[PDB]
Amino acid sequence: SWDKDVYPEPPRRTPAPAPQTSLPNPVTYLTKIFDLLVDRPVTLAREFIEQQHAKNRYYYYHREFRRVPDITECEEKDILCMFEAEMQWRRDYKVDQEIVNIIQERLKACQQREGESYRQNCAKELEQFTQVSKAFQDRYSDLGAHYSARKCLAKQKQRMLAERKAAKE
Amino acid sequence: DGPEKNYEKTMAILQIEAEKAELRLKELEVRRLMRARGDGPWYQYPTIDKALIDHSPKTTPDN
Image 1 (cartoon, each protein chain N blue to C red):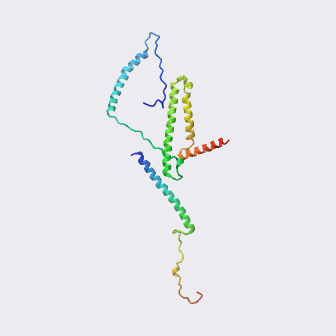
Image 2: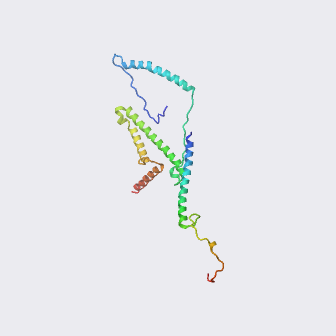
Image 3: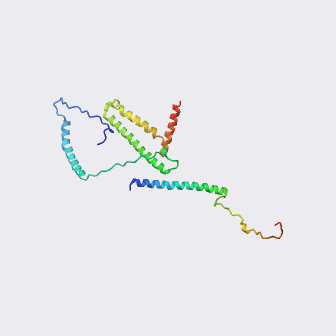
C-alpha cells in the first residue's frame, strides 16, 4: 500500500527449515492451531467487511495548495501578502517536520531489523538522518516559540552574511 | 465550513486592521502638525473679530 521507495524494506531472506531431530517441533503444531482457529475466522470476517466496503465505494481526495510568493518577495507592511507567505512557510515547516519523521522511522526500522549487525548495516540510514537533521536544524532552530517566516528569513540572512565573511577569508 | 472561508476572512480582517493602524498613526501626525502650526481646521483658537472695529470718523483726526 505505502511507497516502498519512501519506506525501504530490504527483501526478506527467511532460511529454509531443515529439522535434524525426530522430535516434532511444537511451534509448527501451535502455528497450525493458531492459523485454523484464529486466522481463518478473522480472515472470513475481514472478507465480509471488505465486501460491505466494496458495495459502498467512495473516494476522498488530497487538497493541493498552489505556491504563493515568499516573504522575501513581500512588501514591508503588506499584511495580505505577508499572511499568504506566512501560511505557506508554516505549511512547508510541517512538511519538513514530516520528512524528518519519515527518515527517523527508516532509522528505527533499520535498528530493529538488522539486529546485532545494526551498527554496520544502518550506515546509510544514519547518514540520511544526519543530513536531514543538519538541514532542519539550520533552517529551523532557535527561532523561538513565536516563530515566523520573517524569523527564518533573518536567520538565513545572518547565515549568508557569515558565509560571505568566511569565504572572504 | 471550508478552510478557504476562514482564509479569506483572515485576509479581510488583516486588511481592515492594518488600514485602521495606518489611519491612527496618520491622525496622530496630522494632529501634531496642526497643533504646532495652526494651519489646519483643527486647533484654530479664536481671535478678535474685525467686524467689531468701527471705522467711522472719530473726534481727533489722528485717530
